Image (spheres, coloured by chain):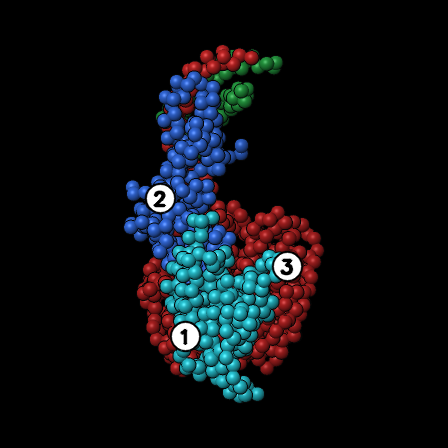
């Protein structure tokens, strides 16, 4: 009822005052507004990856990265321990004692774009059981509730299982590897076997299949690596004659990884028992159409620890693994020294080298145990899992751009020696992206662990992820 | 308002500007209109939450008695920023960020939706005709080529485009609006259209086809 | 209360009050503390106090603008 | 709607110069090139002189691209990308033929599609019956020796796409035979319905 008086009072304009704070608060208003939303997330991620490439890193031990939540009872799984009953059982025993081969008794069928969450577990009786993990993944409570596992299906395999690898490009395909045979299973949406095929490696006498690796980003292409040679087949056309055949002039084959150059063509890295690292550009010249190709190039890595003794680099290597997400090659040697090489995509030369000096919680052990079975959690960049060649303890490593966060996964009680490892990122009841880590021990007990969001979600932050 | 503190301060400052320009005398309004509209166009230009954009555009609309002039100033400001950033990125040869790419794409799409006449008039005004078209198509093609052939091979960061169909639909609606208003550079557009039609990826060729059906 | 006579006085207080609040956010120490992005301190509380006082200014001006 | 009308007329005339670059692209890679023409011909009102120049001009270039006078027909049996572009272009001509202008309640039988009549006249002038006969002779020996995918409509039924998503082009010979037995029927019936067009000559 005083509109005219209100206008007369407001005749002293505050717009000059409004602009004369706004002008000098703009200095931070602009900064916060540009920080708001996903603006700059791409640039932040690019600078984070560049400093990961460049900045030197030191290794620290920790335990807060990984938090156990649930623990299954003993005997939940039957005949988990392999007694190696058979003619090849003694050979497998000798190989595992020599630690040349590592047995992977399970796998997971799940893809970033797919819906599957299947868990395949192998038995000694030549049977692999496919199981649904929906109930296990949806249970986040840390109580002592009895786990309920719904057996999706099962399939008897006519030869001993040493490794199970699900195709990372598509959850549909699962490869089963033993000492001398390879199988490929295409599973239905309910976990039942829809298709079954057998690969024929035509192995020579005295050689054993090390492992079968799917070519990254490639569906029907599988490379079977043995102790002497690698054979690369494409299931889409031929399962008898491999497209590529790679051999090693001297010493035995230990491990094989793959990467792609700037153009995109794949490159195979083979690290041998002699400790030498070799690289090969796969193409028509090196294709199996022209016959076996012997790998000749040798990577030149010069380090004080890496001494070429009696034609062996640190007494031979253990495992090799290139990270597609991190654009960097992991490797380790029999002496227990682990190295991370950032390598040029065009000259194939290591641009930078990062040591990984693993220090145990107890001071009794000085030398670090050898690293093998590198495993990277899909949709969770930076987190890798490895196992010890000599002791078999799991080790979870986060490659921070400036540091190396390592953690040993020790289960209480220690009577249950952990046999195999897996880790899947999935959704929760509250539609939260959570990383659940499933350990299988020798007693058949399952250990359920969970990735600390305050410690394991650096790359998963909205400031580093595009919307 | 659960947003940031400075964002809340900005909302309050702009509603105070509304207070001044709805309560105050006409004299102070016409003195402060220049600075107020300049600051409003600025804050509209730079990235910020949607609420402050909405209130700033409401302020600027209330400032102008005629809607056409208001929308013309908004168009020239934002399109000039787009032109300068695109020209700088093209000249230096850097890879345009996908986020700023989609911001520019959606802004241009909205402008074409509302007034393609003014959009053509400014984006083709001299600050060869339809060079804007050539450069934006070139940027699209470099970004698409930079995108990895397989999403699996991509690292934690994803180079290239993410929502291909939305981007191509926005680009084709831009070209169609320009063809409706401008007629000389059509001989160029045909070529780019055909380049969009022979692309190996079905999700771009078929998307451009169905966009042509829905718009023409 | 009633027809809104209180707005004739309280707004006047707001007229100086935010200006008073301005006389706190213009100092170099205060803006430096803001740039450090620290929640604890009198600067953040006073900026919320501003937000509120010309939020009340909004509450009166919207009614007066819809009084047409 | 005028400005859009000349927009389509120009766009049609631009696409006509770039037809021949589709020689090596591949059939599966080239359907939308003609799918867009299908709309470009929707409001194709024949009465306009510029429009009818555009029509008969495009008919002439598709006829020339088909190359009905080469008579070198022993290569049409095998599967080659240029053969598939022939197949899709004649499928486009077939879709043009099947397009009928729904007339009013008038009893006159001359209310046929202007596009269809023009296509039929052009094909009869170019003499497609001879090519039909030669290609049939070429494929007689072949026959006696024989003893989420994108929306592909209307060139291929969506059921066909969902049944042969691996390759809609595996049955190239069957599709070519269906095209070359179906087209003469339609040109014959449209010529019968039109008194002005003389019936085509057919021998034993």
Regarding residue C16, the answer to whether it shows in the image is: no
Indicate the colour of chain C.
green
Residue pictured at 36% horizontal, 77% vertical: A285
Q: Residue D196: where, in percent of width, then height?
A: 50, 69
Left or right of C28 in this view: D162: right
Give me the disc on residue B123: 2
Q: Please check whether the numbered discs 1 and 2 fall on a single chain.
A: no
> Quick one: label 3, few (<14), some, or many (20+) residues within 10 Å?
some
Q: CA distance from mark 1 to mark 3?
A: 62 Å
Residue occupying image coordinates x 47% and y 19%: B23
x%, y% of residue C46?
47, 24
Reading the image, the residue beneath label 1 is D67
Say which chain is blue: B
Q: Are marks 1 and 3 in contact (CB under 8 Å)?
A: no
> Residue beneath label 3, please?
A133
Q: Nearer the viewer, residue A226 or A357?
A: A226
What tint does the image give chain D? cyan
């Amino acid at each position: 009822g005083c509109r005219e008086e209100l206008q007369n009072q407001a005749n002293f304009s505050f717009a000059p005052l409004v602009l004369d704070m706004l002008n000098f608060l703009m200095d931070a208003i602009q900064t916060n507004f540009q920080q708001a939303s996903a603006v700059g997330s791409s640039s932040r991620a690019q600078q984070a990856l560049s400093e990961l490439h460049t900045v030197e890193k030191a290794v620290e031990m920790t335990d807060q990265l990984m938090v156990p939540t649930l623990g299954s009872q003993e005997g939940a799984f039957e005949n988990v321990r392999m007694n190696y009953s058979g003619d090849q059982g003694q050979t497998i025993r000798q190989l595992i004692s020599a630690h040349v081969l590592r047995r992977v008794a399970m796998c997971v069928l799940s893809s970033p774009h797919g819906r599957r969450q299947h868990l395949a577990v192998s038995h000694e009786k030549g049977k692999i059981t496919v199981l649904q993990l929906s109930a296990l993944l949806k249970q986040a409570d840390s109580s002592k509730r009895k786990l309920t596992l719904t057996r999706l299906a099962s399939a008897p395999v006519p030869f001993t299982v040493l490794s199970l690898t699900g195709n990372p490009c598509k959850e549909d395909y699962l490869a089963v590897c033993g000492l001398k045979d390879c199988h490929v299973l295409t599973f239905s949406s309910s976990g039942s076997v829809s298709d079954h095929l057998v690969l024929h490696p035509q192995l020579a006498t005295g050689n054993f299949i090390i492992k079968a690796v799917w070519l990254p980003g490639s569906q029907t292409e599988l490379a079977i690596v043995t102790a002497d040679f690698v054979k690369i087949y494409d299931l889409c056309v031929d399962a008898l004659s491999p497209t590529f055949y790679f051999l090693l002039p001297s010493s035995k084959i230990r491990d094989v990884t793959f990467l792609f150059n700037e153009e995109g063509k794949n490159i195979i890295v083979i690290m041998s028992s002699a400790g030498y690292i070799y690289t090969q550009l796969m193409e028509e010249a090196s294709s199996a159409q022209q016959g076996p190709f012997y790998v000749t190039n040798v990577l030149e890595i010069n380090h004080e620890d890496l001494k070429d003794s009696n034609s062996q680099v640190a007494g031979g290597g253990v495992s090799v693994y290139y990270s597609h997400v991190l654009q960097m090659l992991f490797f380790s040697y029999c002496q227990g020294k682990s190295f991370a090489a950032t390598i040029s995509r065009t000259t194939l030369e290591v641009l930078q080298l990062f040591p990984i000096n693993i220090k145990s919680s107890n001071g009794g052990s000085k030398t670090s145990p050898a690293l093998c079975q590198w495993s990277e959690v899909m949709n969770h960049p930076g987190l890798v899992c490895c196992v010890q060649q000599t002791t078999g303890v799991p080790l979870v490593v986060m490659v921070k751009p400036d540091t190396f966060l390592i953690q040993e996964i020790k289960t209480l009680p220690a009577k249950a020696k952990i046999q195999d490892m897996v880790a899947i990122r999935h959704t929760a009841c509250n539609e939260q992206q959570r990383t659940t880590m499933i350990l299988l021990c020798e007693d058949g007990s399952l250990r359920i662990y969970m990735a600390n969001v305050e410690n394991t979600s650096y790359w998963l932050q909205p400031s580093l992820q595009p919307s | 308002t659960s947003g940031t503190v400075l964002e809340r301060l900005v909302v309050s400052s702009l509603e105070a500007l509304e207070s001044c320009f709805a309560v105050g005398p006409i004299i102070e309004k016409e003195r402060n209109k220049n600075a107020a509209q300049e600051l409003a166009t600025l804050l509209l230009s730079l990235p910020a939450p949607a609420s402050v954009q909405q209130q700033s555009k409401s302020l600027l609309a209330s400032l102008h008695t005629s809607r056409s002039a208001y929308h013309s100033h908004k168009d020239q400001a934002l399109l000039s920023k787009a032109v300068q950033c695109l020209n700088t990125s093209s000249k230096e040869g850097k890879d345009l960020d996908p986020e700023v790419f989609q911001r520019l794409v959606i802004t241009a799409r909205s402008i074409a939706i509302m007034r393609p006449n003014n959009l053509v008039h400014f984006t083709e005004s001299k600050l060869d005709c339809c060079s804007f078209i050539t450069q934006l198509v070139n940027h699209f093609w470099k970004l698409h080529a930079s995108k990895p052939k397989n999403a699996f091979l991509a690292p934690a960061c994803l180079p290239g485009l993410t929502h291909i169909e939305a981007t191509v639909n926005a680009l084709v609606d831009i070209i169609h609006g320009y063809c409706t208003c401008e007629l000389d550079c059509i001989n160029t557009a045909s070529k780019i259209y055909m380049q969009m039609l022979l692309c190996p990826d079905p999700a771009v060729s078929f998307s451009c086809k169905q966009a042509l059906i829905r718009v023409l | 209360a009633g027809q809104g006579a209180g707005h004739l006085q309280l707004h006047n207080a707001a007229v100086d009050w935010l200006s008073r609040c301005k006389k706190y956010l213009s100092q170099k120490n205060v803006v430096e503390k803001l740039n450090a992005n620290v929640m604890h301190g009198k600067h953040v509380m006073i900026l919320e106090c501003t937000c509120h006082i010309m939020s009340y200014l909004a509450d009166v001006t919207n009614a007066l603008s819809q009084s047409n | 709607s005028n400005r859009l009308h000349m927009v389509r007329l120009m766009l049609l005339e631009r696409l006509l110069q770039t037809l021949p670059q589709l020689r090596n692209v591949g059939g599966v890679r080239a359907i939308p090139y003609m799918q867009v023409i299908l709309m470009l011909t929707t409001d194709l009102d024949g009465e306009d002189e510029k429009d009818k120049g555009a029509l008969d001009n495009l008919l002439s270039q598709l006829i020339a691209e088909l190359g009905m006078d080469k008579k070198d027909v022993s290569k049409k049996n095998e599967r080659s990308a240029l053969n598939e572009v022939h197949l899709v272009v004649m499928r486009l001509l077939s879709v043009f033929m099947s397009r009928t202008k729904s007339g009013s309640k008038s009893s006159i039988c001359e209310s046929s599609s202007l596009i269809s009549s023009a296509t039929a006249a052009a094909l009869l002038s170019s003499g497609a019956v001879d090519y039909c006969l030669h290609v049939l002779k070429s494929l007689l020996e072949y026959w006696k020796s024989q003893q989420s995918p994108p929306d592909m409509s209307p060139f291929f039924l969506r059921q066909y796409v969902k049944g042969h998503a691996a390759d809609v082009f595996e049955a190239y010979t069957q599709l070519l035979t269906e095209m070359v037995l179906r087209l003469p029927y339609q040109i014959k019936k449209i010529t019968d319905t039109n008194s002005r067009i003389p019936p085509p000559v057919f021998d034993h």
